[PDB]
Amino acid sequence: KEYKCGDLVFAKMKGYPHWPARIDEMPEAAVKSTANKYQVFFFGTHETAFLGPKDLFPYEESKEKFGKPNKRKGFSEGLWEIENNPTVKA
Amino acid sequence: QKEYKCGDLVFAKMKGYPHWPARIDEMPEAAVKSTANKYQVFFFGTHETAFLGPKDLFPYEESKEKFGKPNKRKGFSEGLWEIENNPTVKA
DNA sequence: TTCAAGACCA
DNA sequence: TGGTCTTGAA
């Protein structure tokens, strides 16, 4: 489990013996599509979306900052669920 | 912050909305499987490329006894020469 | 269709 | 920050 870029290995392809090989970088496109992509369920609205860590902030650790009441549809409901029904999972 | 875990409570920021109460779920199994434990391997001798899980990888040095013995397949001998003498070929 | 809070972009 | 657009509720 786990390899770094530039590790020397033997690699088994179907039909071939274990073969001398090197670990290279994956295609940038391939990594950008999943590296730091978490799925996010949203309380109140129950929608989800995919997000990177810039756009995520821990709750508890910032409920005075971002927990102030808000008029957008489902927000109050979201502040209730996260504190009262956090495992909605619906 | 980085490396969040499944079930972490967060505020989440989308375009046009305030910082929003959220939970981190699992990604879709398909999406995960498409890049989880998948390395881009380059093969010495042939210089072909593939994508492999750790199942199909064995470190060199640790196993040049087992797997490093002479073989008649196209490019294997060269391959054993390159991994020792020119491991940077990258061509 | 008014207005005010707040969300964007330059 | 300033200026404008949008949301939600009179």
Image (cartoon, coloured by chain):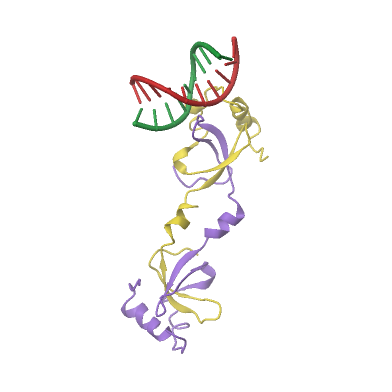
Chain colours: A yellow, B purple, C green, D red
- State the image coordinates of residue A59 (x, y, percent, origin top left): 52, 34
Residue B35, image x and y in percent?
52, 59
Residue placed most toward the observer, B77 or C3? C3
Viewer-side residue, A80 vs D10:
D10
Q: Does residue A45 appear to the left or right of B63 in the view shown?
A: right
- Give above or below for B80 relative to B22: below
Is residue B62 shown above or below B69? above
Q: Residue at 46% across / 43% down in the picture?
A: A53
Identify which residue is drawn at 44% across, 87% down. B69
Give the quadrant of the C terminus of chain A.
Answer: top right
| Residue occupying image coordinates x 49% and y 79% | A18
| A34, above or below A18, in the image | above
Give how far across and how far down residue B75 sits, in percent. Answer: 42, 84
- Find residue A72 and report its horizontal and vertical position in percent: 57, 25
Where residue A9 sits, quadrant-wise, is bottom left
Q: How many marks?
A: 0
Nearer to us in this view, B47 or B84: B47
Q: Residue at x 53, y 46 (%)?
A: A38
Left or right of A8: which side holds A16? right
The image quarter in which residue B42 lies = bottom left
